[PDB]
Image (tube, rainbow over all chains, first blue to last red; front, side, top):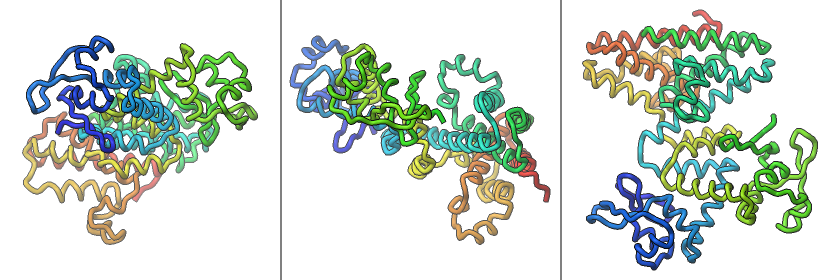
Length: 219
Length: 226
């Protein structure tokens, strides 16, 4: 219950995410004494309990920066993988997203994603509907802000920076994402049935739906 | 749409199939060299794509990445460092970049495939855990299930199960129905926690009340009375 998994690679870690340094040294082809490596590559000297007493430990970002500090046959494989991950993440290769979600044994990481994908689907459906009914320009952003200030309790811009967040939807709990996804879905349905057309009309309707969902606080 | 790939305030205009606008890449990779000369040095095809601004010189995603590691410009170095950071994040199991990858892929089945791989939201589990932390009842499972089911689906648990060929209700449902069900459970858990409902009557009352509120809301959105 302490391992990162990459194909046939096994990297034991501490409870705080530090790699078992001898295993990592095996993976990067590092035959140097760990001390020599610490000096040459600028790493801290620390140990962690991997179930076998204290052992030399190195963090994941230390391991990565080291894989690129090294030119070993093995470290080069890891360099290649970093390059490839950039490309695949850029294209939207969700098989990489699945491997990431599957790699974190934490049930809350996986449920965070499930709620996040409901938010994504509701927002895509809402935007498709708004665009097909004449919304343009800042309409879309406004709807986002409306949906946000309803669930968060403060306006979208202020909350985003108060939490140190670039995109609101990235930093939410599963419940907040579901409330947003629900509001966005209900407004998509409301637009489609009432055939609300125009920036102002759509925004007014979204205000009514989001405000109604806020009123649920009473319960 | 001015389709763009997004990393912080990093904006990369793309074609409908995801190829990059080469002049933008030149900004991001620090290339003041003419694009043609770059094509020569790096072994790239003469490619153009429709970016909503007529045909413009284009470079593929893996080509751009290959350039970031070919170049040593200050800007290219930032892209190299991002690659390293992503290796670290993916290794750790950082699911929020997994979400960002999913959103960069505009195709809706990318989203539904990931949802299929993933566990449910857990809203039903959170509601049942919450009820377990309060009085509740020994057998609330059928009750909470049916209460929400008749709210969102429109028919009793047995009826929904019969009409669509289902053993576990969720087997035959659409995303809207699943979201409405999960939503009811989420807000019900919240109602219990906010009122500190401890008796079974308070808990079941709050669950039915939020279910009724959300039904009435859907009905107004659907403009239906029945």
